[PDB]
Length: 211
Ligand SMILES: CCNC(=O)c1nnn(-c2cc(C(C)C)c(O)cc2O)c1-c1ccc(CNCC2CCCCC2)cc1
Image: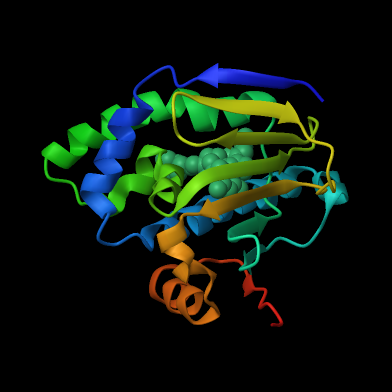
């Protein structure tokens, strides 16, 4: 019930600027990066389940779901990956923004393609192209469920979460910007998944809204 607040102990500003000046014309990249993040976490639980199958006591189905919500202007991406402990959450959303931005900027000068963003540990922040705010709910076997949240300003919060428990994995909720509601369209999400994520080795399921 207690909220901790962290300062972006680098320039998340530098990262955000790089991302605008690199993908603002092709915002749809965010879905590719988020889906790819899920796949990595999914690989991790799969791998770990081999040495020790009780790892899957928290859930057997290894998959990714997309869930637009036009009423709430949210697009949510759920996976049953290995999830994140507190430390992993901070590490992956804080510590690695710093070193990852740096590493990526250096490679971009040396001439690397922008499509490499994922490999430098910062693909998640491409969500700030479409979303004013992002919430990340996550659960790892070796820890409690946590909610991370940030508007990409100078800070993010981490709190123990108390809403519906997932058993293992990560849900990213994007509160879209007024002008970016197109990513709530079934047709659009379809194009994107086909265009970017056809070779993801796990089922990606779009949950269509009734209307
Ligand atoms: C301690 C082990 N747990 C995890 O690794 C994990 N668990 N869930 N996720 C995860 C994270 C995100 C972002 C919020 C960071 C996500 O959108 C979906 C996820 O499943 C992650 C996760 C953590 C980090 C990353 C980023 N990997 C970038 C890396 C860079 C070097 C090349 C290979 C790939 C992707 C997913």
